[PDB]
Length: 118
Image (cartoon, rainbow, N blue to C red; front, side):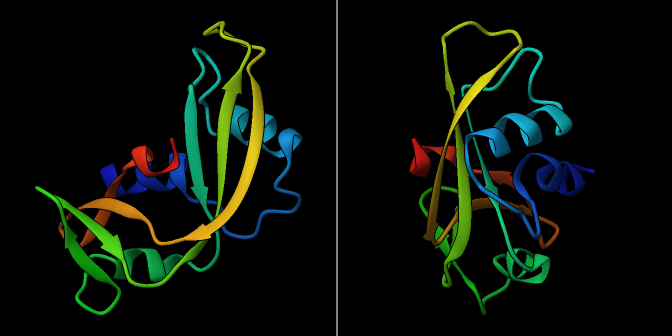
């Protein structure tokens, strides 16, 4: 549930064109439009590497109670443009490639630290 929800806001396997229109589309169908999110990042690629971040293989402790991946991930950060909190929600996209900071529960990712993408 909490895991399954992490995927909803933060996982997108095989995206097409990670541009502005990509954010506005997926932000809508992931239900982050009304009222919209200021900022939100999607990890791409194979699911199993993201879970693995809660094991010793692809993860380290991070700060007080977080975890940060060994490997890097393709990523798409979607940032709100236009101030107003309700749709239509405008987004600028920024693609990148780096490790991720997450929280874990029962060996499964249940939280993304957006601060690293701020």
